[PDB]
Image (cartoon, coloured by chain):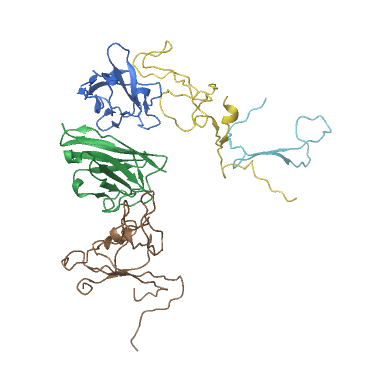
Chain colours: A yellow, B brown, C cyan, D blue, E green
Amino acid sequence: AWNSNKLDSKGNYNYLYRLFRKSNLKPFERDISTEIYQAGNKPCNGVAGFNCYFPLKSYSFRPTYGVGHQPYRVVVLSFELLHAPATVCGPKKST
Amino acid sequence: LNDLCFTNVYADSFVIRGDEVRQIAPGQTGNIADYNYKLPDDFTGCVIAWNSNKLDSKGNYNYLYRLFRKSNLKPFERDISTEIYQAGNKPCNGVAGFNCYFPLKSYSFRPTYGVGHQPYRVVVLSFELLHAPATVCGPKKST
Amino acid sequence: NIDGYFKIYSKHTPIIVREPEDLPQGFSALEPLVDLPIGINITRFQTL
Amino acid sequence: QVQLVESGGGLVQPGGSLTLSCVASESSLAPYRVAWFRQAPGKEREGVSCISRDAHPTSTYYTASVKGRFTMSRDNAKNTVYLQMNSLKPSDTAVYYCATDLGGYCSDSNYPRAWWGQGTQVTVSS
Amino acid sequence: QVQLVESGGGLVQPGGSLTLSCVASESSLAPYRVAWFRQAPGKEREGVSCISRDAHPTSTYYTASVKGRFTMSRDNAKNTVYLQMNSLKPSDTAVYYCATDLGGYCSDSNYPRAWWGQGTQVTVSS
């Protein structure tokens, strides 16, 4: 992880995070279904409705929320050791 | 214990109530155990204690206890502390005043307590096998 | 393909006679060319 | 299908305290968020407090008018949530309702509103 | 540096029940002992009950006036100690404070008194 709030923040609600969805996460899954949560017997077709809200919500990139809620760049790299012929090995040097 | 040979056994002398000798076990604290005497996480020794009641009873405060210790101690340290607890914002300089208690309190040595936590002096050792060559070794006899 | 490796051997040489019936009698050594670390389970072969 | 019951309201003096309860029956509110609403006559229903399924302070939301005075706590075994009032004002005099949905987490402006109880009358007057 | 927030107190009838929450913020109370104090007007602050870092009843202490009636419970996840209120009597009417220090183990006479909260008012009457 590192700090990216100074350059990423201007706010920019392009990277909106899903809040309403069917259930919790399972390993190795992608959350791309932009489907409105169904919390009632009545189907949610027909845009917004009572007790059925779109998962999209603001996630505080406004400049007012400076110290908090500003974007921090975090990346996680999966590493596999002794499973396949290694392709990424570290530097040696010396000549 | 006599057959095995130990190395550099260190003995200490403590005076206690007797009601909490059981609690001097590692991981839990008793009144005196949290006050003055502490034992390690896993001490390598045996506990021995005789009935220090009849003979040690003469009101006697020369073995008093550190009631107001500033904080919990650390492994293998003594209790040479001899000043007062810190609780307020101003220094306790100038004997007992507002919000400070002197740890010098009666640890119930009166003659009327013939059944109340009479002195139950306990001695505890700590050994070492295989850590260093033994000095005090058990007997074999038989000539 | 074995133990998560894929090796390819190749060798090229000219030909004397246009005989397509049988392989000419000559010794040829197949040098390793490319090695791959993938672990695909392969069972069938297809040509284009 | 779940039904709720609001109780504990009554005639209290200004500066007093009250403790409401939203009893749920026939259903479990443990995996679902619960919100408190009040509606005095003459004004539209407004949010008061919102507790989530995790009952975490981060997921715990109160409205501006009740910050620092109103507190909730949900007991999952009994399947009920409270709305503890401290230092009640006469402006708090309203019919308090509790609502829940299939959602599990509240937001600053997202409160469950599906199944409402009969409500309780909280009156702050001499 | 740690600040505490007492809440849950209020007007109760004799023999009533309550639960006082000592909210801890900016610091973790898990490795440190927590004690409860009450101070009604006209009398000095008096120790009510003390809970240690190990939450052990050997290390959990109640004063004589509160034995058998008052109870604590601490959940280090939310960083707050409770004070269960049972068989509340008018003599219990006091401003209830909670205190903590760097010590982690209570005693029958040693209660943490370093950092204090604002206190909660508990009144037992009609």
Answer left or right for A25 relative to B12.
right
In the rendered image, the quadrant that contains the C terminus of chain D is: top left
Horizontal and vertical percent for residue A35? 45, 18
Which of the 4 image quarters holds residue D68? top left
Query: Residue at left 31%, top 12%?
Result: D43
Relative to B127, residue C15 above or below: above
- Which of E38 and D98 lies nearest the eye of the viewer? E38
**Percent x, y for residue B55?**
21, 75
Q: Residue at x 25, y 22 (%)?
A: D4
The furthest residue to the front:
B94
Figure check: B63 above or below D55: below
Quadrant of residue E16 in the image? top left
**Toward the viewer: D108 or E10?**
E10
Give C17 or A34, whichever is nearer the viewer.
Answer: A34
For residue B22, above or below residue E64: below
Is D93 in front, or is E69? D93
Number of numbered discs present? Answer: 0
Residue A33 visible from this viewpoint: yes
Q: Position of residue C4 (x, y in %)?
A: 60, 40
Rendered-image quadrant of the N terminus of chain D: top left
Residue that extends furthest to the bottom in the rendered view of this protein: B143
Q: Position of residue B135 (x, y in %)?
A: 42, 78
Q: Residue furthest right?
A: C16
Residue D63 visible somewhere in the drawing: no
